[PDB]
Length: 273
DNA sequence: AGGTAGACTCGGACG
DNA sequence: CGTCCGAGTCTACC
Ligand SMILES: [Zn+2]
View 1 (cartoon, rainbow, N blue to C red):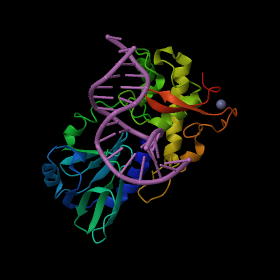
View 2: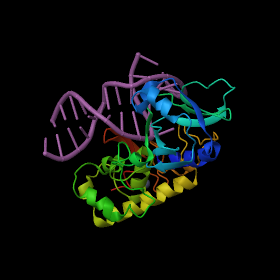
View 3: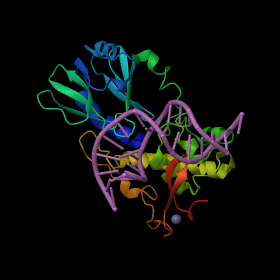
View 4: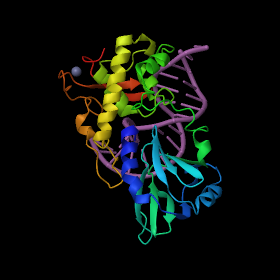
């Protein structure tokens, strides 16, 4: 999940948990709990707190409780559902928050890659992992100037640059590849090789792509669905991601896939330069 | 120095 | 039996 997927999960999850009070926290894979590292302390401190809100920062969910914030990263396969305490759990359920009304928030993650951090609210933004994040791409804090400031200082590939959450928060392999296609820039280009015009164009397409994907409920390409189990529809608007061997939608040249920044990377060798 | 490739956390779907 | 994976950290290598 990237920004659009996490944001869709946020909007669809909030009404199902807001105002509910935690009475138990059960943990079946402790490695997921990163702070406090002692999973018993993590569980104990949340008991008796009420969910007051749910925000997103980059690819993170931030649950706002009474004293604390719970910062959750889904990584590749993490997802949440709300269901009755009376029913058997689904496979791969690793953390469960039980509410006083007999409902439960369940965290499932087949690959076990996801993470959870709990801090007092006032500390959440000045500790890892949130402290080092770059600006929200749908905010005025993300501008061409912000992009250029980092790009001019490094010969790393532009793909490596955009995947770096300290540069700007929210883009991953799908939306990086798509943004670069739409801006007409090859993903292996050294960041410092980009012109001012290219940087402006890239910023414009990054904002448009990520905004469009939010409106369409994210991209369902393998396993992502919203909190109600509904697929997104942005996957029907992809130009390059997952389309290797198929004709480019704009020029008909077969889409290529190769390694860039050590990752599978999709591009049109004609539209991108 | 300042970069990339890819092993690793993990498990399952697909030739 | 090998390869792939909406993330991210880290090592090995150049
Ligand atoms: Zn093309």
